[PDB]
Amino acid sequence: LFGAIAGFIEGGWTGMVDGWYGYHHQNEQGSGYAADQKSTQNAINGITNKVNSVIEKMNTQFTAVGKEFNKLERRMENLNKKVDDGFIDIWTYNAELLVLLENERTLDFHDSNVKNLYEKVKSQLKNNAKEIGNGCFEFYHKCNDECMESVKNGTYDYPKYSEESKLNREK
Amino acid sequence: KVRDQEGRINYYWTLLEPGDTIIFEANGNLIAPRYAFALSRGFGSGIINSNAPMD
Image (cartoon, rainbow over all chains, first blue to last red; front, top):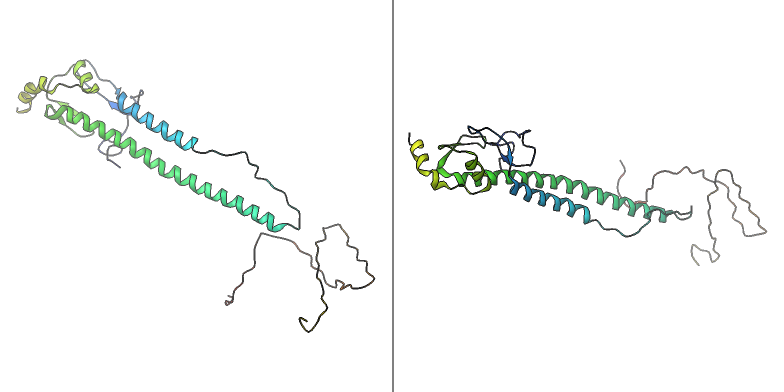
């Protein structure tokens, strides 16, 4: 676990409907909910390949399990029963454990993606913004929709607002 | 000679289904049945070859 989901970020947003991970901004123009398309798309590709790897790795040949034996062949019937029960037990154990462990792999993957998004935004903003907990940043400068979109796609231009942020911070 | 004897007795068995008859015809060399066993069957089990106490 990485501490983002059910961690320093408490709960999810029912408002964000276009993706798994994303931002919620609040400016003078208004607030919103935008999903991070790059991280969400990477997660979608990974989860799709995991599901496909689980499904398509099972290949079988045409077989018929059922067999019939007479009364004088009971060692036959018992051996057939043994092979059938053994295969069923092995497959049941394997399937249950595989699902159990892959659920933890998927949830950890989502937690890591959220934390990585948080760290990316933090490294972009540097000291131009303050961390106020809950995965939430407060800007020392004045941002419009261009600034918010710039933070979102990954082209923030810290030097543009460095001076104003310094003036507002040291006050 | 085995068990003091040279002659041999071959032992045979079969399971009569409920609602069936067995007919023995013999002009000699018959070791006839005297006691039979009505056998209701159960779960598959086995025979353990051991020398251990029983509790």
